[PDB]
Amino acid sequence: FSKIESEEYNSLKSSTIQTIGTSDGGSGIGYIESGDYLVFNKINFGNGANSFKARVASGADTPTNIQLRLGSPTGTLIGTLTVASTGGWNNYEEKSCSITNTTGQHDLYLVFSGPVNIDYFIFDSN
Ligand SMILES: [Ca+2]
Ligand code: NA
């Protein structure tokens, strides 16, 4: 549940997504459109996690939400990270939001409401 690179998803649903280069020679996911989602099979939150942090970039004219659901694309919604513009598609920063205390192993789904670039995300226990 610690740190997960979004380019290393197990599956996804989209007709636009592509693996892009992120700042500092890193890799990530871009060309996301409303409705798309990334799937990360069997993530183990262990004893629990109540925080979500993601390194994202956005040069959009409107904010984008990243819903965090478990089990399926419509699964339990444990949190939603709203990503306001960061001034550019290559202006990456870490944004955090809380999530309902989640424990054990689950299949993680990230559902997007629009375009945003995402490098990696982390689950912690604040
Ligand atoms: Ca990455
Ligand atoms: Na995008």
Image: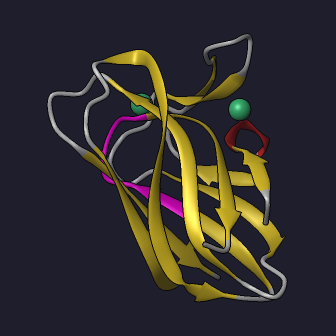
Q: Quadrant of the C terminus?
A: bottom right
90 vs 83, left or right, is right
Front residue of this view, candidates 87 and 19? 87
Is 77 contained in the magenta span? no
Which x, y percent locates residue 125? 67, 74
Which x, y percent locates residue 121? 64, 49
What residue is shown at x 67% (from left), y 64% (from top)? Answer: 123
Residue 74 shows up from this direction: no
Q: Quadrant of ligand 2?
A: top left
Residue 93 shows up from this direction: yes
Which x, y percent locates residue 35? 37, 54
3 vs 90, left or right, is right
What residue is shown at x 53% (from left), y 75% (from top)? Answer: 69
Q: Is residue 111 above or below residue 42?
A: above
Front residue of this view, candidates 94 and 27? 94
Q: Quadrant of residue 20?
A: top right
Q: Which residues are magenta?
A: 110-116
